[PDB]
Amino acid sequence: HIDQLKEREYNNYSWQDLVASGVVEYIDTLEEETVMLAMTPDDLQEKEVAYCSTYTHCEI
Amino acid sequence: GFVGIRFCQECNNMLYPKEDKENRILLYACRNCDYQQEADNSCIYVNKITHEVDELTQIIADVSQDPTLPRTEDHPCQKCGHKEAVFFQSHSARAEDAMRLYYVCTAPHCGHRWTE
Ligand SMILES: [Zn+2]
Ligand SMILES: [Zn+2]
């Protein structure tokens, strides 16, 4: 996805493609209360003291 | 012990209690209908000042499949003996003073719950 997006502008690739591909998702304030949000993808998932290990989403 | 509502047989309405003065027994009459039935519990009302409610009776087995709930491996289940298990406080208002956890097994077809 990153490679296909970095070559945008030139061809035709945009955010709608990411949304349709199933990588991002719109979570509203009422649903955000029932998801294990994560701050960064790398730091908060490697392998350490078992905090939750059940992250569902991750912020940009 | 507690007392539950028992509806009528014909009109299906609330049955109020009645102390039979003739036979000296407890009856449940109907406001509208004239139905009668001999009682068996010998109780009418009970009040729980301390409100000693067992939180385990409110907890459900579906809590296990919660993505935003902690899990521990040091408190395995009893019946099935699975390792993974969840834990959480009462999560109910009017908590007197206790953060005692309520461990629930995290595995299908078990739904067991316990406390330590
Ligand atoms: Zn009746
Ligand atoms: Zn179990």
Image (cartoon, coloured by chain):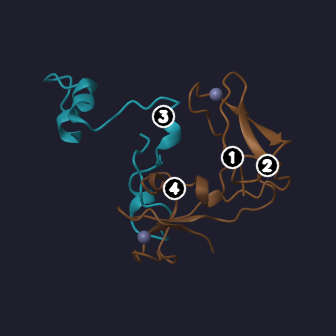
Chain colours: A cyan, B brown
Q: Are marks 1 and 2 on the same chain?
A: yes
Q: Label for residue A31?
A: 3
Chain of the residue on which disc 4 is drawn: B
Q: CA distance from mark 3 to mark 2?
A: 57 Å
The picture quadrant where one finds residue A46 is bottom left
Crowding near the residue tagged with mark 4, few <14, some 14–19, many ≥20 C-alpha atoms within 10 Å: some
Q: CA distance from mark 1 to mark 3?
A: 53 Å
Q: Position of residue B64 (x, y in %)?
A: 45, 57
Instruction: Specify the amino acid type for callout 4.
Output: Leu
Q: Position of residue B7 (x, y in %)?
A: 61, 35
Element on which disc 4 rests: loop
In the displayed structure, would residue B55 be above or below residue A9?
A: below
Crowding near the residue tagged with mark 1, few <14, some 14–19, many ≥20 C-alpha atoms within 10 Å: few
In the displayed structure, would residue B69 be above or below residue B27?
A: below
Q: Which residue is mark 2?
A: B25
Q: Are marks 3 and 4 on the same chain?
A: no
Q: Are marks 1 and 2 in contact (CB under 8 Å)?
A: yes
Element on which disc 3 rests: loop
Point 69% across, 21% down: residue: B32
